[PDB]
Amino acid sequence: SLSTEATAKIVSEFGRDANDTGSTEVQVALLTAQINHLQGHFAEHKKDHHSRRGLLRMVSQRRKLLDYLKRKDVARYTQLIERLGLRR
Amino acid sequence: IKVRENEPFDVALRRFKRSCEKAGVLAEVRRREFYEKPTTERKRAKASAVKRHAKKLARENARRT
Amino acid sequence: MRHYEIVFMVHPDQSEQVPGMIERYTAAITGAEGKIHRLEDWGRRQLAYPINKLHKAHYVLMNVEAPQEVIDELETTFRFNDAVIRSMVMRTKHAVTEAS
Amino acid sequence: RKQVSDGVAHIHASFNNTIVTITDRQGNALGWATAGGSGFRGSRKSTPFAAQVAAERCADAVKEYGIKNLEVMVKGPGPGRESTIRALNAAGFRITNITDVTPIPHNGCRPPKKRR
Amino acid sequence: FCRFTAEGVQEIDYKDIATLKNYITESGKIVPSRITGTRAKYQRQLARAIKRARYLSLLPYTDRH
Amino acid sequence: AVVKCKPTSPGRRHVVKVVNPELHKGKPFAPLLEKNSKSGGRNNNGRITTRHIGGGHKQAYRIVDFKRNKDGIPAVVERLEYDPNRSANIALVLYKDGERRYILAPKGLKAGDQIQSGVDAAIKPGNTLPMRNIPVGSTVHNVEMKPGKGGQLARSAGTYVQIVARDGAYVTLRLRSGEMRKVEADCRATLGEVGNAEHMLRVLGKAGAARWRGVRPTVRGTAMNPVDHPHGGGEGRNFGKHPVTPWGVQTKGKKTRSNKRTDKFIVRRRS
RNA sequence: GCUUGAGUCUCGUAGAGGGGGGUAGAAUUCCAGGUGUAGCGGUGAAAUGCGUAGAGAUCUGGAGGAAUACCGGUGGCGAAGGCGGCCCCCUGGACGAAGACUGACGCUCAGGUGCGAAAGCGUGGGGAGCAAACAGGAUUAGAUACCCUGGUAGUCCACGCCGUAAACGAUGUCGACUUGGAGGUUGUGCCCUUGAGGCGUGGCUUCCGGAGCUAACGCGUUAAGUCGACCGCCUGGGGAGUA
RNA sequence: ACUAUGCUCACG
Ligand SMILES: [K+]
Ligand SMILES: [Mg+2]
Ligand SMILES: [Mg+2]
Ligand SMILES: [Mg+2]
Ligand SMILES: [Mg+2]
Ligand SMILES: [Mg+2]
Ligand SMILES: [Mg+2]
Ligand SMILES: [Mg+2]
Ligand SMILES: [Mg+2]
Ligand SMILES: [Mg+2]
Ligand SMILES: [Mg+2]
Ligand SMILES: [Mg+2]
Ligand SMILES: [Mg+2]
Ligand SMILES: [Mg+2]
Ligand SMILES: [Mg+2]
Ligand SMILES: [Mg+2]
Ligand SMILES: [Mg+2]
Ligand SMILES: [Mg+2]
Ligand SMILES: [Mg+2]
Ligand SMILES: [Mg+2]
Ligand SMILES: [Mg+2]
Ligand SMILES: [Mg+2]
Ligand SMILES: [Mg+2]
Ligand SMILES: [Mg+2]
Ligand SMILES: [Mg+2]
Ligand SMILES: [Mg+2]
Ligand SMILES: [Mg+2]
Ligand SMILES: [Mg+2]
Ligand SMILES: [Mg+2]
Ligand SMILES: [Mg+2]
Ligand SMILES: [Mg+2]
Ligand SMILES: [Mg+2]
Ligand SMILES: [Mg+2]
Ligand SMILES: [Mg+2]
Ligand SMILES: [Mg+2]
Ligand SMILES: [Mg+2]
Ligand SMILES: [Mg+2]
Ligand SMILES: [Mg+2]
Ligand SMILES: [Mg+2]
Ligand SMILES: [Mg+2]
Ligand SMILES: [Mg+2]
Ligand SMILES: [Mg+2]
Ligand SMILES: [Mg+2]
Ligand SMILES: [Mg+2]
Ligand SMILES: [Mg+2]
Ligand SMILES: [Mg+2]
Ligand SMILES: [Mg+2]
Ligand SMILES: [Mg+2]
Ligand SMILES: [Mg+2]
Ligand SMILES: [Mg+2]
Ligand SMILES: [Mg+2]
Ligand SMILES: [Mg+2]
Ligand SMILES: [Mg+2]
Ligand SMILES: [Mg+2]
Ligand SMILES: [Mg+2]
Ligand SMILES: [Mg+2]
Ligand SMILES: [Mg+2]
Ligand SMILES: [Mg+2]
Ligand SMILES: [Mg+2]
Ligand SMILES: [Mg+2]
Ligand SMILES: [Mg+2]
Ligand SMILES: [Mg+2]
Ligand SMILES: [Mg+2]
Ligand SMILES: [Mg+2]
Ligand SMILES: [Mg+2]
Ligand SMILES: [Mg+2]
Ligand SMILES: [Mg+2]
Ligand SMILES: [Mg+2]
Ligand SMILES: [Mg+2]
Ligand SMILES: [Mg+2]
Ligand SMILES: [Mg+2]
Ligand SMILES: [Mg+2]
Ligand SMILES: [Mg+2]
Ligand SMILES: [Mg+2]
Ligand SMILES: [Mg+2]
Ligand SMILES: [Mg+2]
Ligand SMILES: [Mg+2]
Ligand SMILES: [Mg+2]
Ligand SMILES: [Mg+2]
Ligand SMILES: [Mg+2]
Ligand SMILES: [Mg+2]
Ligand SMILES: [Mg+2]
Ligand SMILES: [Mg+2]
Ligand SMILES: [Mg+2]
Ligand SMILES: [Mg+2]
Ligand SMILES: [Mg+2]
Ligand SMILES: [Mg+2]
Ligand SMILES: [Mg+2]
Ligand SMILES: [Mg+2]
Ligand SMILES: [Mg+2]
Ligand SMILES: [Mg+2]
Ligand SMILES: [Mg+2]
Ligand SMILES: [Mg+2]
Ligand SMILES: [Mg+2]
Ligand SMILES: [Mg+2]
Ligand SMILES: [Mg+2]
Ligand SMILES: [Mg+2]
Ligand SMILES: [Mg+2]
Ligand SMILES: [Mg+2]
Ligand SMILES: [Mg+2]
Ligand SMILES: [Mg+2]
Ligand SMILES: [Mg+2]
Ligand SMILES: [Mg+2]
């Protein structure tokens, strides 16, 4: 469920400091980090539908933060997506 | 289950069996307990238990006996 | 990385090899970072029921920290070996001591 | 001829029958009797006394072997067994120990359907 | 009586069988909580340890082996 | 793997191809293939002894090693190839000292995997061993019936033998027929299952596809005249005869096993 | 802007949450082998069935499949369907503790899309037990049933379909608010652990009851009370959830 | 053990 070193690495990069860990910029990166880690898990398995429910929670949770971020500030919205590799 | 009873005694006395198994093998796994029926017959045996226990507190009525 | 608690049992005649067996399994794990926390050979203990039509197995508790690559290589050496009568590998919750 | 010291009286007590079978120490049959073999047929075959008389009929017909003392190994439920062991004393034996071999399956095979 | 002790807490372990054999009946079956006290949390740990001990042939599965 | 073909023509409607992408797209390794001329069913005396064989695509023989001796020499699998001579696909194994040879491709094998053969080795799919060294209750293939020979049993796509027991010098094997056959423990067996298990799900789809596999049409006895086949004649779809071969021997339940030299080795016949 | 809703991280706690792989013991059937002598089996009572070719019973050694006794509870987890031997692998959520951060990011949702017991269906495995269909013996006025002896699809597995159930608390989701008692379960505080305790306060949960509501039955801080947001649905019975 | 049925309408 994402190691503490993996979260702390992303937290102390996108945000201001290690203290700041709840920004829309940070939150979207932690979801994206976990969603990509789960693609290996759903490459095989496949029938694990209960875990997919948690994944599809993360996916929809991400899009509501991104859609919030776009309406709030278009500048940092476009800069965040280029770094993470979203919008396909 | 394995009951020797020393030497002078004999007279069965094997409640060790009767207060352990017998009913478990027999009147349960003799004929099929249709998955749901246990869930039904337990929950009524469970509801009948607390029906008596809740009444046992309110059993102290007038009586006059 | 992860802590484990390996408890395997060995056939009576091959109990003389167990001093050697432990040295081989230690060398596998101790090379890859994680140390062995406990060494306790239980000895030729009686079985509750016969396994493989015999009594008296030679029990060995290791208890060790290791990565997942080494522990599964050790798990495979138990199945491809007629000397070892059964084994099991428990999870983490830190290291321990004593108890028998 | 043989002349065994001790044996094992296996009792297979089902609801319908009570099959007594006296064997030796190493599970090797010496003789037997049944509630159906005693006479007692139909409703009479499923009773405590019809098992008693079957054990009395199994008590003799193993006198050639000359068993002094034996172990009981009851099985199934049945109306017998709490009556059949009484018969082994009254006949002429010494019961060393009484045991159960009632085969308890640890939820294994689906039993037959309930009857109406 | 209840759990381990006043300042016990601890965790019910499978290796020791002296304290563990008190929590199984003479046949080999597990004794329930309503006979031997015990909080539900430790009765689950106990049950799990009895099964782990059974696997290693430390405790027996039954007395017809 | 099993791809169903779109119905752009009748006889392309029911076609179901076994496309293996991991197979080789190029010419095979020339030193290990000689020519293989076709019999058309006929023998020494030029007479059709086996009916319904004739024609098909010209196909060269790969010199596949079944015995698999060359001991104590690890060998890297270079590439998985097509074999027209066989149900199962083959693997071009490059031995560390610089030989190449073909082997039957097991299930879990790929271009890059390393394989060893001999007495010691490791218990892993592809590694040939004597069946004495192999664990009881394990899946093998390419099994020898006699020590030192090639490999008779379990060489067809998806096929495998399971080792049931080991009585001293003899090993009891449960074959894919269901027959439990006793073989010598010194005999060798390549570990795992034979690959290309999708082979069975291929469906040809046209009459032509059987022709280019070297099969010729089977004519039914009932169609023929009395002179030709025991089933024969009748004025419009008659029979009234117990099923039989063209040579009168009863088909449809009639044991023709009569070896009697090898009946000692068969534990239980198949069912 | 703000921070109370909502979300993030931090350290843990419980759990048949899931998916993949192993392995254990009891038992059933069967397989060959030893013993052994007439029955066994079954039933309301019988018979078909099985047995002198030596069954049943008993023991020895295998093989295979499926399901996990006891723990086990008005216990737990899951959105629902549902989920119980033990062990590792990957993995989703829940809750608690005190902070720090974001700064309304929220709630509902027509269409859309996913998951969805059992039975079915398709291709390929497996097949002990059980068992629709089916057969025979009973029962009966008849018995295409109930009972008995046999018994194939199926139940198991892998992968696709199906998309329904009294899929039920017959109770849509989210939020706020309004007397109590006895418990179960899992947290975390304060105190002497001074001895299986003393005292709070969060989750989830079962039972009884107050006002209030209800046609009544009952519901009743987990509302069917008092209100708000949005959705779904209803408009006599048959015809018909049919054409 | 199992064990069927009761032709129509009629109490302001
Ligand atoms: K389904
Ligand atoms: Mg997450
Ligand atoms: Mg999380
Ligand atoms: Mg910020
Ligand atoms: Mg919106
Ligand atoms: Mg149920
Ligand atoms: Mg010539
Ligand atoms: Mg020639
Ligand atoms: Mg010639
Ligand atoms: Mg032909
Ligand atoms: Mg030609
Ligand atoms: Mg050829
Ligand atoms: Mg050919
Ligand atoms: Mg061929
Ligand atoms: Mg020799
Ligand atoms: Mg032909
Ligand atoms: Mg044909
Ligand atoms: Mg023909
Ligand atoms: Mg003609
Ligand atoms: Mg001719
Ligand atoms: Mg002719
Ligand atoms: Mg004609
Ligand atoms: Mg005709
Ligand atoms: Mg005719
Ligand atoms: Mg003829
Ligand atoms: Mg003829
Ligand atoms: Mg003829
Ligand atoms: Mg046949
Ligand atoms: Mg604040
Ligand atoms: Mg929340
Ligand atoms: Mg704690
Ligand atoms: Mg769990
Ligand atoms: Mg877990
Ligand atoms: Mg789980
Ligand atoms: Mg699981
Ligand atoms: Mg699984
Ligand atoms: Mg077993
Ligand atoms: Mg068995
Ligand atoms: Mg024979
Ligand atoms: Mg025989
Ligand atoms: Mg008769
Ligand atoms: Mg007859
Ligand atoms: Mg006869
Ligand atoms: Mg016969
Ligand atoms: Mg005979
Ligand atoms: Mg027999
Ligand atoms: Mg028998
Ligand atoms: Mg056996
Ligand atoms: Mg087995
Ligand atoms: Mg819950
Ligand atoms: Mg719910
Ligand atoms: Mg795995
Ligand atoms: Mg949730
Ligand atoms: Mg989360
Ligand atoms: Mg808090
Ligand atoms: Mg703002
Ligand atoms: Mg601020
Ligand atoms: Mg909706
Ligand atoms: Mg909708
Ligand atoms: Mg679906
Ligand atoms: Mg499903
Ligand atoms: Mg589905
Ligand atoms: Mg199903
Ligand atoms: Mg099917
Ligand atoms: Mg079909
Ligand atoms: Mg087929
Ligand atoms: Mg069958
Ligand atoms: Mg049946
Ligand atoms: Mg039936
Ligand atoms: Mg019928
Ligand atoms: Mg008949
Ligand atoms: Mg009938
Ligand atoms: Mg009739
Ligand atoms: Mg049957
Ligand atoms: Mg299963
Ligand atoms: Mg599976
Ligand atoms: Mg699977
Ligand atoms: Mg669908
Ligand atoms: Mg729907
Ligand atoms: Mg519906
Ligand atoms: Mg339901
Ligand atoms: Mg319900
Ligand atoms: Mg309720
Ligand atoms: Mg409804
Ligand atoms: Mg919703
Ligand atoms: Mg909360
Ligand atoms: Mg009231
Ligand atoms: Mg109202
Ligand atoms: Mg009222
Ligand atoms: Mg309510
Ligand atoms: Mg409130
Ligand atoms: Mg309140
Ligand atoms: Mg509350
Ligand atoms: Mg509410
Ligand atoms: Mg309400
Ligand atoms: Mg109402
Ligand atoms: Mg309407
Ligand atoms: Mg209407
Ligand atoms: Mg109408
Ligand atoms: Mg319709
Ligand atoms: Mg009539
Ligand atoms: Mg009438
Ligand atoms: Mg009338």
Image: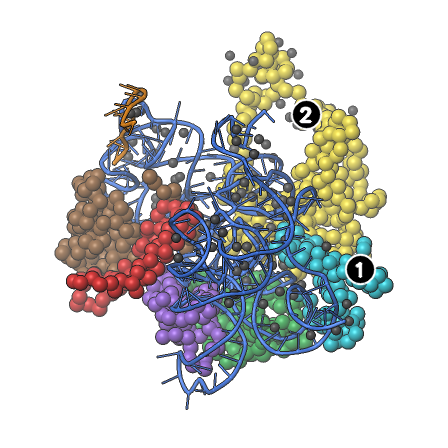
Chain colours: A cyan, B red, C green, D brown, E purple, F yellow, G blue, H orange
Helix, strand, or loop for circle 1? helix
Which residue corresponds to the image point at 45% horizontal and 64% vertical from the top-left? Answer: E51
Residue under mark 1: which chain is it in?
A: A
Q: Nearer the viewer, residue F66 or F213?
A: F213
Helix, strand, or loop for circle 2? loop
Q: Nearer the viewer, residue D67 or F10?
A: F10
Q: Quadrant of residue B8?
A: bottom left
Position of residue B61 relative to residue F49, above or below, is below
Which residue corresponds to the image point at 37% horizontal and 71% vertical from the top-left? Answer: E37
Which residue corresponds to the image point at 26% horizontal and 62% vertical from the top-left? Answer: B59
Q: Is mark 1 within 8 Å of ligand 5?
A: no
Circle 1 packing at 10 Å, graded few (<14), some (14-19), many (20+), is: few
Residue under mark 2: which chain is it in?
A: F
Q: Amino acid at mark 2?
A: Arg
Q: Which residue is mark 2?
A: F51
Q: Which residue is mark 1?
A: A71
Q: Is mark 2 within 8 Å of ligand 10?
A: yes
Q: Nearer the viewer, residue A13 or F140?
A: A13
Judge from the rendering whether residue D50 lies leftward or rightward of residue G211; answer left or right.
left
Q: Position of residue F115 (x, y in %)?
A: 71, 57
